[PDB]
Image (cartoon, coloured by chain):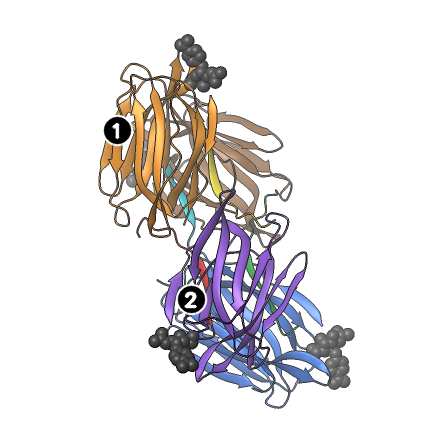
Chain colours: A yellow, B cyan, C green, D red, E purple, F orange, G brown, H blue
Amino acid sequence: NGKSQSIIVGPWGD
Amino acid sequence: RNGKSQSIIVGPWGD
Amino acid sequence: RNGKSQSIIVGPWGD
Amino acid sequence: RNGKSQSIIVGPWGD
Amino acid sequence: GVTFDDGAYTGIREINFEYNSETAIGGLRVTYDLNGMPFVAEDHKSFITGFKPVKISLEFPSEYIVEVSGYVGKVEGYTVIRSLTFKTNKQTYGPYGVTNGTPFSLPIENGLIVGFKGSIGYWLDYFSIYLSL
Amino acid sequence: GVTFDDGAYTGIREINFEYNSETAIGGLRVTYDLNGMPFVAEDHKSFITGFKPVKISLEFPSEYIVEVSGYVGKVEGYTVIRSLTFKTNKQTYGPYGVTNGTPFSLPIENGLIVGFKGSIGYWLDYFSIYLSL
Amino acid sequence: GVTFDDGAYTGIREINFEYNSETAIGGLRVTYDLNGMPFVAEDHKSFITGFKPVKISLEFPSEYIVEVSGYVGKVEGYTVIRSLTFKTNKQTYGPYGVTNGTPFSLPIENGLIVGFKGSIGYWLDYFSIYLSL
Amino acid sequence: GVTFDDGAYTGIREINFEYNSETAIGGLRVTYDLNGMPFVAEDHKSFITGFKPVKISLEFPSEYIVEVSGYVGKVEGYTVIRSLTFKTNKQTYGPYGVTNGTPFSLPIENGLIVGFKGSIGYWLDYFSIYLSL
Ligand SMILES: CC(=O)N[C@H]1[C@@H](Oc2ccc([N+](=O)[O-])cc2)O[C@H](CO)[C@H](O)[C@@H]1O
Ligand SMILES: CC(=O)N[C@H]1[C@@H](Oc2ccc([N+](=O)[O-])cc2)O[C@H](CO)[C@H](O)[C@@H]1O
Ligand SMILES: CC(=O)N[C@H]1[C@@H](Oc2ccc([N+](=O)[O-])cc2)O[C@H](CO)[C@H](O)[C@@H]1O
Ligand SMILES: CC(=O)N[C@H]1[C@@H](Oc2ccc([N+](=O)[O-])cc2)O[C@H](CO)[C@H](O)[C@@H]1O
């Protein structure tokens, strides 16, 4: 799809 | 700038 | 997705 | 090495 | 002409530009996607008028540009973009402008156009494309 | 809590957030850089008040975050971020909040933080970081 | 210890490493994917022996790491990685080593580990991770 | 022709290819940089012989391609790449082959070529380029 992807580093605090 | 491709590197763990 | 890293690839020239 | 995110840009056409 | 640089965004929702069947491409205005919400970028106008506006409304996520092509040539002595064709994964927004001169094309096998930059005077002098995954 | 997702931008200019020396991190508001111009993202408010706001104004281009760290622990029966520390290439914006619980750290050897997402109720429940070159 | 840096690849196929239930993590050897075929990286050896090797064979394409975590502590006065846990989208390769000391974790919401670098003497001194889409 | 796809690496060290001053581009073999060391990719051979080889060795590190251009035209009825020119930040590896037909070009404002893919029969039918920071 036309949505630019990003690198995201997992949540901290959950 | 040079011909070496760059990468994201997440800091070291263990110091 | 899958474990394969993706790359930007600019279309072919020369058909 | 600055805080400005970089982008791949493919040269101009018509110049 | 006057230079411009929209910068990079997360996608493209709409492309509005001018063209003249006898000259070349005129002004250009892009509506990008910025993290899910529309972001209308600056309108880069031609120094003159008398153009035929075209509004390419893309069905953002499912639809995206897979190739940009056109013709480069001289008008009044200036080398400018005279024709443009935007091909998406759904359809082709046929040639607009004068399809004469030197052709050019940026087909994209993998990746997305996420920004435009360039220059515009009476006509689109030139442009560059931001690419990203 | 109420989830939020700022999305991605081209850098960070300012980070404002609340903290309480006896509880944990409160609300959060980030000013990103978007192609050279500041972009103030939505303010993510705490359900309550009584916090001590802190405004970290980075000297965008030269200065950027090289590490985010802090502590995770329980407050009123909820697991939340109790402390935060933002280290840039210029200085360290010392610990804010309660430094008790489980430590976490995201040191960045190469790359930039370009966005935040997470959840906030009475306190910062959790958060994630967008990374990019 | 002796520093190492495998650099970046297109993915991870296998991770071989040593650990000792009384001390810490030892040597490391990763088999990456390089454009659809395996690429065995250099073996980064511990200065000593007496370790228990573990071979994590990922079903490449379909399986990939979503979180790396472990413990950091002192052995003979040296700060080293004493434990490691690799969680994939299919399963968890249980704790290996001594789960005592300061915990650390790199959960990955979106993205892939495409390389490792660090230092190893008697034990894994420290390590960094290459991330990419 | 027969397709090929070298995949992506960290840079380009050498480009060797064939050409015929009366027909078009023939076989191609690229040596990439993979994390500081060379990686000689597979030789993609033409179905025939009678070509003139050209070997472009780049001063790694410092030297890199900033633009690839050439000509596309028909030979024996087939549309193939007839000419190639590689311009780096140091110099231009002048036109090789027949410079007749339709010109094409990929100028790179920012980024690096990190791989090639395409198809080769008697001659180079077409090719694509991997781009990365
Ligand atoms: C001063 C100025 O900005 N001139 C621009 C402007 O130049 C013209 C000036 C006069 C005429 N004319 O027909 O009289 C046409 C273009 O547009 C050109 C193509 O878009 C170039 O951008 C050119 O640099
Ligand atoms: C409904 C709701 O969003 N509640 C949130 C909210 O929950 C609380 C409800 C009551 C008290 N209290 O002290 O009475 C505290 C937190 O805040 C928590 C920590 O930030 C969680 O986000 C929790 O999900
Ligand atoms: C000189 C050297 O490389 N020493 C390394 C090496 O240090 C020693 C630890 C134990 C002995 N010993 O004789 O028992 C010697 C060196 O290993 C450490 C943990 O991996 C560190 O890497 C330390 O830097
Ligand atoms: C079957 C096959 O792969 N044929 C290829 C092959 O076709 C030819 C067959 C015969 C001649 N000939 O001169 O007799 C030339 C090309 O090469 C072409 C250009 O490279 C195309 O790749 C064409 O698809």
Where is G16 relative to D14, above or below? above
Q: Which mark is residue G60?
A: none
The foreground one among G69 and G122 is: G69
Which quadrant of the figure shows ligand 2?
Answer: top left
Quadrant showing the N terminus of chain E: bottom left
Image quarter of residue G91:
top right
The residue positioned farthest toward the bottom in the image shown: H22
- The amino acid marked with disc number 2 is Gly
- The amino acid marked with disc number 1 is Val
Q: Residue under mark 1: which chain is it in?
A: F
The foreground one among E55 and G133 is: E55
Q: What is the CA distance from the residue labelled 1 to the residue labelled 2?
A: 40 Å
Percent position of residue G94, x then y: 54, 26
> Which SS class for mark 1?
strand
Q: What residue is at 45 percent from the left and 84 percent from the top? A: E76
Residue D14 appears in view: yes
Image quarter of residue F50:
top left
Q: Residue under mark 2: which chain is it in?
A: E
Number of numbered discs overlaid on the protein picture? 2
The residue positioned farthest toward the top in the image shown: F76
> Which SS class for mark 2?
strand
Percent position of residue E79, x then y: 45, 80
The foreground one among H113 and F119 is: F119
Q: Left or right: where does residue F115 sit relative to residue G114?
A: left
Percent position of residue A9, x then y: 46, 36
Where is F20 relative to H9, above or below? above
Percent position of residue H17, x then y: 56, 77
Q: Would the CB of label 2 be found within 8 Å of ligand 1?
A: no
Q: Left or right: where does residue D14 sit relative to residue H78?
A: left
Residue E105 appears in view: no
| Residue highlighted by disc 2 | E118
| Residue highlighted by disc 1 | F54
